[PDB]
Image (cartoon, rainbow over all chains, first blue to last red; front, side, top):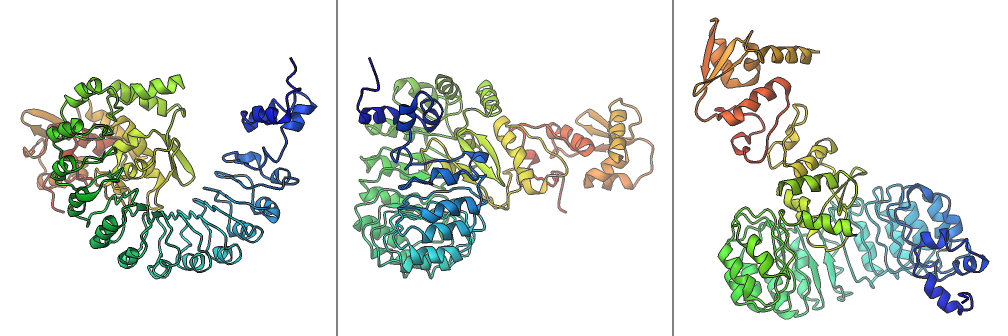
Length: 372
Length: 102
Length: 103
């Protein structure tokens, strides 16, 4: 029984089921043939070198020296290489697609400049908590490589005004957007960029200073899917009504931590909402009155999230527990206004619920950690 | 339960089986998913929207690391320990870490 | 350091000797000194500085509770507190307060 008589396709399919550590540490010393098999464009076009700390500083010269089709560079949580060690790889970058580097503070705008001018093809630029990332490099990023299709620019307080307009006039193929607590973001950069590409599905502007003057004009596009407008500045209610009445295709709506937003929106969200799938209402000031409407007038619901609710109706929660057919997602936390019956009876009455109470999710977590 | 709280506490102070990772000034606390949900509504805002196995959170530059360190032990032990040098930034008993309206 | 002075005074206090100012709460007597309570709680300096007597007897309103009261003196002395979640509200002022306490 010789394993090396198998065709190379089968041997590569076998070797693809080993991690990079296993492949480069054990299977590369067995013999010449296995070492030559564990070195390909197959295994070296999806790098994913995240959190390899102080081991890859000048080594990036060899990973991309003869390799021709790196497309999935991932150096997230890097703390070893410098601008030189990333620009040397950035010089070639043949058809890079999904550059990703989170929390790599030592990287600066020089790396962005190196990666943005040597590959006119890109699909994902999901950079992260890198500070000192000024807006001069993103200008040329939008000017030279106008093929990028997805950005992520959280926690970079240097993207104030020029960046959005510069990758809004040239680039048009963007699909997803995500932003974080980035100050100095003006409203006069998104209103113009609201008529070119209406194919956006995911929108996230958490902790940002976008005024509702651009949210009002969102009625134009009718293809939006997911919303992440958390802590937003007084978005228009009638615009939300129109987008939920006309756009039947709507996936997610978070709207958490908003205080000027009133009870009317959640009162009316059960009037016609049939395809709504989850709701994240944490620390909401609900007046424990929409539960009757959300139980009686809603028949299609599977995810419900109760946050820091000071008051609640145990009878209503019990009624809605059996009112639905599959709505079992009670992740209760810090609910002081609770009895000791539901947490004692519904655990065994419904053996298809996980729950989230403190008394239960302490032994289960230890048990699942010990098993795996 | 109480012994459940202590067991979770030790498992936190094992650096093993930690879900949520708090990133403040390069320093990284490693704690669970459920407990920080019980602690401060600000965090449970940023967790429950994801079912990802590994999570990451950053905090505003306003929240200080010196006052941040005792808070984790607060959350894990439900215990109060204080010194006269470090009070003003925690002066609401809703612990008022800078921004920080729950 | 003067904290050595504070700790020495604390240990002397925790012998029921060399104690100068006596606090009375529904019968319980808690002994302490003259200078330190003047430095700690502004309600106390009011009733103290106006006399030069020997033995003092200061009573506290029902508004101040014993259960929070024992750690108050401890935090006055050594700036360290012990407290759990059940007894918090009658102490939630973070500038001590708790006494009158319009400053």
